[PDB]
Image: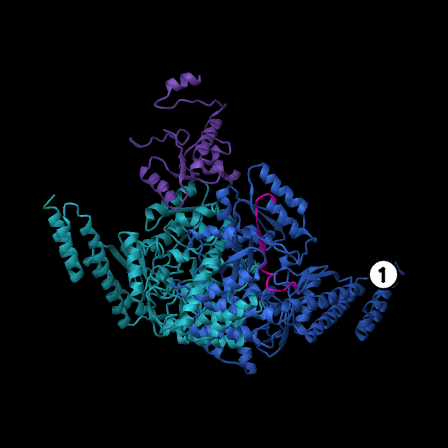
Chain colours: A cyan, B blue, C purple
Amino acid sequence: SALACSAHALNLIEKRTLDHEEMKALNREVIEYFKEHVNPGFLEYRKSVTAGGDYGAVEWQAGSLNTLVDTQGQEFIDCLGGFGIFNVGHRNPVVVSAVQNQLAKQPLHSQELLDPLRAMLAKTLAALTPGKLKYSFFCNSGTESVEAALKLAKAYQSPRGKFTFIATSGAFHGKSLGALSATAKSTFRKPFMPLLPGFRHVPFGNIEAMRTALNECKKTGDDVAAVILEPIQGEGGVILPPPGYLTAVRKLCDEFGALMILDEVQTGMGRTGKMFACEHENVQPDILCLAKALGGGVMPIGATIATEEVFSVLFDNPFLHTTTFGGNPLACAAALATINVLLEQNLPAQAEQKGDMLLDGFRQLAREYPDLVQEARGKGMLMAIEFVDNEIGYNFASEMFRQRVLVAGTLNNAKTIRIEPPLTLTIEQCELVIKAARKALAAMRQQVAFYEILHLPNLNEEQRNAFIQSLKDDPSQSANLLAEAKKLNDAQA
Amino acid sequence: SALACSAHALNLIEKRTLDHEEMKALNREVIEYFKEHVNPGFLEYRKSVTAGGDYGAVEWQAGSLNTLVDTQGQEFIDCLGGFGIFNVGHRNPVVVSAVQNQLAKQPLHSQELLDPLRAMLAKTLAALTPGKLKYSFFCNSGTESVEAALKLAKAYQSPRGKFTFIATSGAFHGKSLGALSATAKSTFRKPFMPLLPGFRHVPFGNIEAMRTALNECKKTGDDVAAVILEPIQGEGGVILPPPGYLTAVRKLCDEFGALMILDEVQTGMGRTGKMFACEHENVQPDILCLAKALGGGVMPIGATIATEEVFSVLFDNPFLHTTTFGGNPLACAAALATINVLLEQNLPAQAEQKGDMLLDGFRQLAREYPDLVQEARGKGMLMAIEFVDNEIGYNFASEMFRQRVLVAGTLNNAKTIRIEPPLTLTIEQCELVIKAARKALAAMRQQVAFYEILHLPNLNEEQRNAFIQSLKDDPSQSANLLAEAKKLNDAQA
Amino acid sequence: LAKTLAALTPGKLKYSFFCNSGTESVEAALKLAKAYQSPRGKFTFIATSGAFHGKSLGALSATAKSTFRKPFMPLLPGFRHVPFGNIEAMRTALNECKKTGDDVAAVILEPIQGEGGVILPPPGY
């Protein structure tokens, strides 16, 4: 019965530790259900099952601020941070109690009485945001964030006869039909077409291009309502735009009277060094999208902050754009807690020193294995290593998973991996990571070399065997023996 | 500073009671901020400020399961239930601890490791849902619910060459651009047009119409992908469709190979008498949208449950439709708690007896004041009273607000008011409500009559004064004195 | 005529369709491209700014002047304009569309923009 299934899951919430067969039990239901009620695919493409072991790595509870412990007790260092969620770490004590307090009083609002925390957050965000960004709208996610932004721009610009929206190729903005009209990857968009009419993509980091789009549209009577872009393409592979770009986009917008929308969903809340990435070039957008880390990894939340000139649209009919759960008290709680922590222990500043020590650490590794890595890149605690193959990439992401270091990448989309550990990552865990990636890079180089030695056609078995022998006895020579085998295979060529 | 504003709001979370000037202080910031950072409009159109009093009615904390207490200590009976959110009441002790437990372990997931509660919920929902509905997708709201539904239908039906979507006039489904393409009110849609191409509306409760839409589209090569409707139009004014309709829609769909999407966002989780409204006619949709009350008024959540045949689309590329926060552990917690409570204290069954005692109670009041009410209507604990004017309606919703009974309606959209108290409303509070609405209906009838006596043109001041005199001395004669004044005004006519 | 035109036209141009005007000309062209390319999953059409191709709703979707188009919008979905004589631009349009899953059905242009003011494109264009 559903009554049955509810209770069994209800008692498991209460349980805090597990007998080894209580574990086995669990992991087998959880795989069983994932296959029959969730998606069977996540069992196919995820690194938690491929490299799971005998059992998958089913989540259990948070370890420290930076660690995660599965149902077997294995503790993982999070260098994923839920793709930019866990900026203040897992269960940050300051956020968890702000939530638990608010939970004692009133978790959600009535929707009729002026709820106080939504004012306080709207206020704080006004304070925290650059230039004339004043009004906040509150939703539940990063996609609802962008949607409302699109709606604001729309309601603003359509009376002025402007309907077209420029977005950028490689841009991600959300999976809901409205945001998916601005999101750019082929794969994500094609099945659900036709999407919103009038969304046109230009290359990212290309101001010369965006002028031509804004101008062509002008000429043909399809004038641009708004331009929407991320400060850094996060999912897009940690693409950094050319210095001056965001500033130059900002003028270009101002020149053509087009609203500028900044999707700071993955670069907001101090990840890139500054509280908002658009502060590195000190650029003020007309609209700013926030989410993910705004909810301190405790709560889900999305905020849309805009200038007064733009948010005015909603003033005369405030019900034009509502949401049911948006701005609920205990989500509010969470953010104010997160906003407080970020300014107190001043973690944007931490983001920049840990963010360069790490990244440098990776582009060093990247010089030492140019045969497995094209490049590493990032800005503050948002960074990514680009491998040569998805084969290799998924092999890196997977290898370290076993070294109990949790990074990105799935079975297929894995050519470039992303490193996004909490901003609260210690200097001790910082090395432990670059160390783990060095071991990982060694072992892969071993395997890569290993095959290389085998299809050497001119090389005979007698010689090949000598190399394979010294390879296993000395994996350090994986590069030397290789060169010696290739040099030998060419000798008999 | 933002650091400053964060802390002040942070300490207020900690505070549990307020000195009367600590109150005054609060309510004035909260109004001040709402005007300068949230919306000034909500101060114009909401009943919390118009009828606020000297101060507005700023929320503070939950009272009992059915009561809410503002910053002045005034306790309100919730006959709104957050528009169908608070189905198991405010802070239902069983939900709050399931949440607080899960909060001690891990609030959000890593997105790499198989999270156990999302299996358990996916499982339970499979159990709880009629027919072949098997797979659940998890999002954050009611709008994200429908969006994914639209996306499932799309990804299913577009390979089969079907792109058009029929929705119904009066339908509400969400404010995000995708759902807003199916949502039907003019007001909500117009500013943001052009929306998704290929959405066509037909009248609700009209099977004769929907045949013609499905057939016309067939003829013209624009074959219907899916039909989407609510079992009852909730926001649409508690519109009940003709018996047999939902069943007859279900065949019509099956006949034209069109997917049937049921928006049980506001009629789900036991409000109408059954766990899902589509069980009264025992109809199984291809897709089912859930939200609101699924989160036990503690958490925000949305679920999209579908048949295997349909959810298969996502199997081969499970990342086609993801969301960042969807299915997070502590939202999961909340639902399983809510699902458990609803089956335990068997509250759908409570919904039907309280839902008829109330509603009958209103259509009685409705016979006694036919000059202020056209009709009352509902199905289980979803019900609404329809007045004659928005003037009158906002006057009812507002009047009772002061009688500390919290109902729907805003300053303008208020012709029909909705009654949606928690399913945990006691029989004692049940009368207290019908009583409060009787007082309210009296006082309005007084005022209505009062003006009626004044523009009686043939009536002189001397006579008019006698009526006004007895009116104030005996408001019960408001009907009698009126008839006597009108009869007198006609005597001098 | 179908024969003669086959003779008169360069390369593998073989079949002629006959209509009544210059606008009906382009419309059918758009229709041919469409019926050809939509089974192959290609729906977008690149045209050029300054281009004139016709005043009927289909051709007017490819015609480019603001004045001529605005009152009758919304026109055919999926028509995007690039500057004329700019091969560097048209690559980016064809490529951006590729990336976003909106692959280009056909590109339509005049050899010289006539009404467009006798615009001559760069040699090689």
Single out the residue that lies furthest toward the bottom: B19
Answer whether residue B264 is magenta in the image. Answer: yes
User: Residue, x 35% and y 39% (percent of image)?
Assistant: C90
Does the magenta stretch mainly form a helix, a strand or a loop?
A: loop
Percent of width and height locating residue A30: 44, 64
Q: How many marks?
A: 1
Magenta segment: B255-273
Work out whether residue B204 can be spotted: no
Q: Is residue B143 above or below residue B73?
A: above
Residue that numbered label 1 is attached to: B458
Task: Please indicate whether residue C87 sits to the left or right of residue B62 in the image.
Answer: left
Task: Please indicate whether residue B483 sits to the left or right of residue A99 in the image.
Answer: right
Work out whether residue B363 can be spotted: yes
Q: Secondary structure at mark 1?
A: loop
Percent of width and height locating residue B20: 57, 82
Closer to us: B196 or B5: B196
Position of the C terminus of chain A, as image quadrant, is: top left
Residue type at mark 1? Asn
Position of the N terminus of chain A, as image quadrant, is: bottom right
